[PDB]
Image (tube, helix red, strand yellow):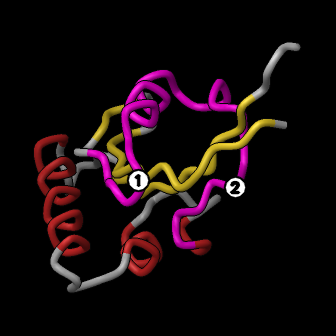
Amino acid sequence: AISVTEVHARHILLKPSPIMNDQQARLKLEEIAADIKSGKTTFAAAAKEYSQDPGSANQGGDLGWATPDIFDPAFRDALTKLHKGQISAPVHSSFGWHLIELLDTRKV
């Protein structure tokens, strides 16, 4: 009986640019993360304000349900280690830098 596990993830993406190099992108995510953790903002509000992924920014960063092989492998690796409520440290993918949360898992 072969299993298929879907994950429910959310994230905030920042891409480097000429205004924002890689160091500035990572440190900005650290500042967002500490704002979420200190109740200055919610994860969803920050996703809406800052996330540079237009496929999810307006849905509070929500990625829906998916088998995790759809994700960049660095994103997938980080997702694997996360407990309920926990936000990742900033994670680099081919897309830029991410804050990641694992919301749930299920079998389909």
Identify the residue at image location x=59%, y=62%. 62
Identify the residue at image location x=34%, y=53%. 14
Label 1 secondary element: strand
Q: Left or right: 32 with respect to 23?
A: right
Give percent across and percent down for residue 21: 17, 45
Q: Left or right: 55 with respect to 53?
A: right
User: At label 2, which amino acid type do we have?
Assistant: Gly
The extreme right residue here reads 1
Quarter of the image for residue 107 reads top right
Q: Earlier in the sequence, mark 1 or mark 2?
A: 1
Eye-nearest disc, 1 or 2: 2
Residues tagged 1 and 2 counted as in contact (Cβ below 8 A): no
Q: Left or right: 17 with respect to 69?
A: left
Residues drawn in magenta: 60-88
Identify the residue at image location x=32%, y=33%. 92
Identify the residue at image location x=36%, y=80%. 42
Per the model, the C-alpha gap separating discs 1 and 2 is 16 Å
Task: Report the disc number at residue 89.
Answer: none
User: At label 1, which amino acid type do we have?
Assistant: Leu
Give percent across and percent down for residue 80: 45, 30
Q: Residues within 10 Å of mark 2 (few under 14, many from 20)?
A: few
Residue denoted by label 1: 13
Name above or below for residue 1 compared with residue 93.
above
Label 2 secondary element: strand
Task: Report the disc number at residue 64.
Answer: 2
Count the numbered circles shown: 2
